[PDB]
Length: 18
Image 1: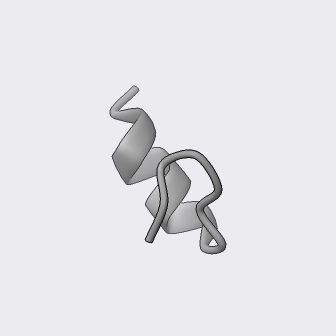
Image 2: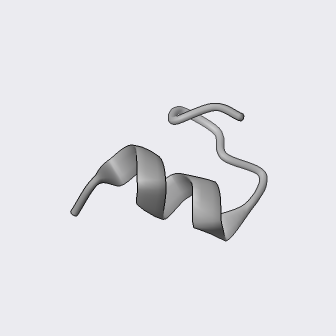
């Protein structure tokens, strides 16, 4: 997983911690 380029939408949200 990568917060800069999360392949999975779920990862982006988790990494974004909004």
